[PDB]
Image 1 (tube, rainbow, N blue to C red):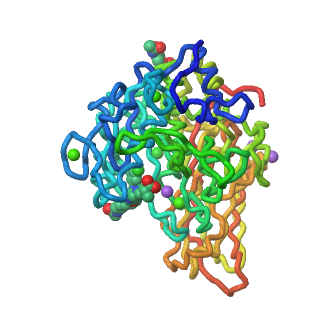
Image 2: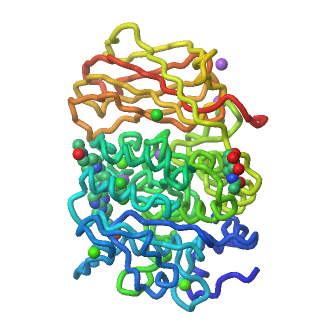
Image 3: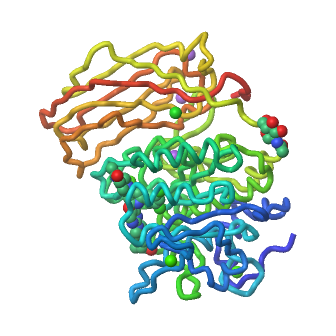
Amino acid sequence: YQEPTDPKFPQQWYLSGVTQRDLNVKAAWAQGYTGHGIVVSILDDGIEKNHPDLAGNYDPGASFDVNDQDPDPQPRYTQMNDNRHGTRCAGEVAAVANNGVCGVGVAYNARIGGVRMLDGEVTDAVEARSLGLNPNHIHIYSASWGPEDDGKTVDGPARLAEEAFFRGVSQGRGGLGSIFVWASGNGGREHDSCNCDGYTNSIYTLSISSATQFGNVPWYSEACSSTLATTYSSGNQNEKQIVTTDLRQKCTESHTGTSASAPLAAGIIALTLEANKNLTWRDMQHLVVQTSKPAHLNANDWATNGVGRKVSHSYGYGLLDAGAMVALAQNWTTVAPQRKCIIDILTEPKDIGKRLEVRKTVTACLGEPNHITRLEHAQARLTLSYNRRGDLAIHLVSPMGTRSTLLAARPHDYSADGFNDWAFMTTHSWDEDPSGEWVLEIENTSEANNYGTLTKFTLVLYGTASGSLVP
Ligand SMILES: CC(=O)NC[C@H]1CC[N@H+](Cc2cc(Oc3cnc(N4CC[NH+](CC[C@@H](C)C(=O)[O-])CC4)nc3)nc(-c3cc(Cl)cc(Cl)c3)c2)CC1
Ligand SMILES: *[C@@H]1O[C@H](CO)[C@@H](O)[C@H](O)[C@H]1NC(C)=O
Ligand SMILES: [Ca+2]
Ligand SMILES: [Ca+2]
Ligand SMILES: [Ca+2]
Ligand SMILES: [Cl-]
Ligand code: NA
Ligand code: NA
Ligand code: NA
Ligand code: NA
């Protein structure tokens, strides 16, 4: 295998590292996987389709302009270079290799497009028309943004966008399901808690957080239980950043944030789909769970779950490992059809006060076609009132003892509107047997005499009843 000759490839430390602090992408390339035949679309502020490092891989069939309602996603050029982010992300996935320009994409032979959707009012329809763009041509969608990362917002896809997610994973990609890759958020300095973002909190999105070059949790990271894995991104000013294509036919060495991590994951997923084009949207999440690597990622919350995997709310199952992903994809057996077990927990509303614990022993739909012995995602769908929402911290403990943080305290969240059937999601009990006692904890983290009521707690289990590995 001959590694890329591009002038800035040596500066793409998260690929070309010889120190083991990288995404192990060269190993995938050396197995023959470069993204050939795979189609990725960047949902953002547009894509400079004539960029010298993107033109050779540019695919109009992966592109649209929902802001101006035309097929051409070219960015709006301004003095401050406002609409450059989509172009930066496109190059992370699929910048051309061995052409004397900038560096390379993770999947440097994949086809790449962009949806111009963020340069205008982002409505439910705009979101739905973007997520649902050409779903039998585009394999993988990359989205780096969502509701405001101000640490006080609770919002997610409205009706059309949620319908687009279910249509995508159900009928997209020939029935195998669109793969939606999401950044878990940039709200770290606002103490944001990312299950409050219904896009990254969705089971239908494969959610990605960031690690700095030295293996630390960056200032901008949000912790939450819905995150699945991690890719490198920026950190302090002694740590390197992401190197990629930039607006006006330039390169950049200063692409940053969790919003730079999701495209790298999308590229790794593109290599993996080249290795096995029959992978379903759920198969891809299984591969990520099984192959991601905690080693050398620093966090104070690494915990071993019930099947022996380390999980963190900052990192999910750890750093993506592209060589391992493509190796395991090749002979992967398609997972069984997805089951869903609905358990309405409360017999009466419960006063929260200073602290509430709800314990329930469940059989996970024993005797039914939705019996689950092998969990994938789990949700605690909660309806509650509270006088100051951000004073609440919420945890969910599985029968195997895995304590998922569903919500951390959010000091800026002064809302008195509570949670209205909010489906807090955790990935940390993946492959556990969910039969047994679940424990929900709601606590007032403030010394204030806060008050409210939990009126509904639905435990929703997804998964299967076959195919488990030895822990
Ligand atoms: C009841 C109803 O009908 N309820 C409609 C709302 C439902 C909730 N939704 C949330 C939402 C807001 C949002 O709002 C924005 C707007 N704009 C940005 N931008 C633009 C500026 N950019 C500058 C970057 C520069 C500084 C740089 O390069 O650093 C940052 C990102 N981000 C988020 N997006 C998304 C979204 C983003 C992507 Cl990607 C894909 C999809 Cl599907 C949805 C979603 C808004 C409409
Ligand atoms: C894809 O997987 C399905 C489900 O196991 C199987 O029926 C089908 O034959 C597979 N197709 C290919 C081309 O491998
Ligand atoms: Ca246009
Ligand atoms: Ca190049
Ligand atoms: Ca957030
Ligand atoms: Cl469902
Ligand atoms: Na965000
Ligand atoms: Na997700
Ligand atoms: Na444990
Ligand atoms: Na059990």
